[PDB]
Amino acid sequence: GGLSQLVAYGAQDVYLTGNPQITFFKTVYRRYTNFAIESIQQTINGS
Amino acid sequence: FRDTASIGFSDTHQDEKTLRFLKKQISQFIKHLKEYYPNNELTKKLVMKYSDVQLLPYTKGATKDTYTSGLFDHTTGVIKIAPRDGLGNVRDEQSLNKSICHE
Image (cartoon, rainbow over the protein chains, first blue to last red):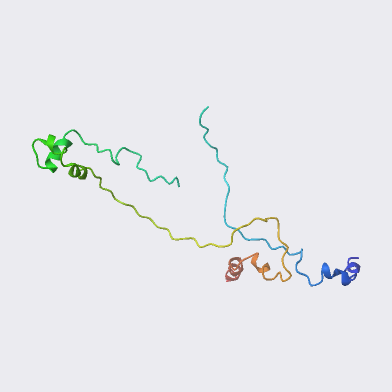
């Protein structure tokens, strides 16, 4: 299974996973300012 | 938030008095035949045409708030040491609340 791929690690992978910087499995989302959106109708002048 | 400080009525410099105002000027001045006073003293007549104002204040401080510029809003793969931004998914509010509710 998948373990057989993890072990297939070589010098070449130094540019992919060696000295790792990130992961993909623990997303950290950003907190953001409180806001809300309201749809409002405008008055049209003229004819 | 329209930013219109205007009164919007004819009261700023309209001078809504009657014709009796011309007699009041003779009360402000000292005369009986004013047809020769403004032809000579125009500065005093300009001094008797000035409005009295009242100013208005308000103040609110400032909002020093950093953390802006949210362009890329898709997602962001966490760094290797994820347990530096990982314990931020729930702040200390919903972490201290669950401990206070134990009593």
